[PDB]
Image 1 (cartoon, rainbow, N blue to C red):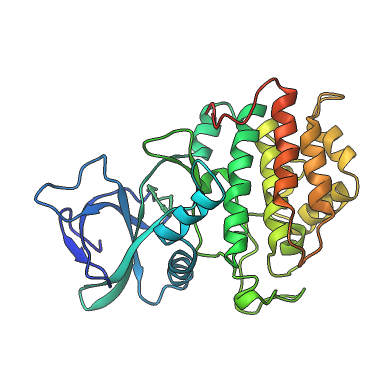
Image 2: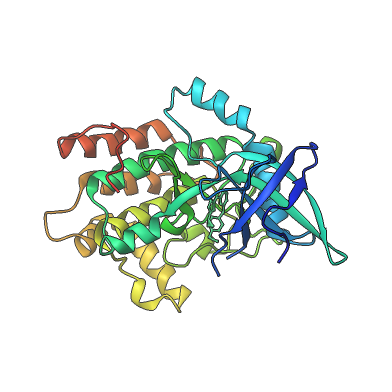
Length: 320
Ligand SMILES: N#CCc1ccc(Nc2nccc(Nc3cc(C4CC4)[nH]n3)n2)cc1
């Protein structure tokens, strides 16, 4: 156990932080945290501290993403310029080194969040409403556009990596950048082929055809993953979920259902009850080339048409 409840840690910018109670479930070593003060760190703490040994690969990858793309002023400038209500990218508050029993450990200070969507999804009998799925997806498209414009792809979008704002249950954030991928370092897109440094293939039921083909993740892959998430949230199932131990089967089902999206709609939704925006979204992502920049605004309009169809609008209400 890396820290004590009430321990004061100092980051590389000489900012002092006070450690609170551990909240890391089973997953990484995470404690509640706040700015150093006379008062103890409470249950309402606005930060978390993530700790791993200095030699940990994913913490270095995650730290590099947050340092490069998630500086508080970087996010706020984007929110302002793009005229967004918020941006679901967690803010980076500091990082440092800590020693315990001779060994060296790396820590990161980040935003504290509420519940993950997987818990809420399971509590709602493995279903999310059309309104909830469209509102979630509009915000995920904002997150994905931002990280893609900052040379990164997530490659592992799912309900367990989507956490609600502790103070606002209508604001969803995308977490876990330990296996995030820098697809175009210095504006140079990675060629269609395997990356020897990368070992991860995402989460089998949601991962992209590109990842299944052993190719490094790109922008179209992240949008494809979101597509599968949308179907799973709307129906409580995916056609290939009964054979997840066999990646060959999962890739085969994905390749065949990409070739015929109408058969995917017929399989997942009751006859003539399929949401048109889901099919239109899948058809648009299908048209993307490996190195192609997505037309994010066009994908947003597709989802906005779905909200208009159900007599709603983008009011930012997640209704879950
Ligand atoms: N344990 C566990 C699962 C889990 C593991 C890692 C992350 N990563 C991550 N990245 C950036 C910010 C942030 N904030 C949190 C995390 C938690 C609780 C303790 C889960 N609260 N606030 N978390 C989120 C959930």
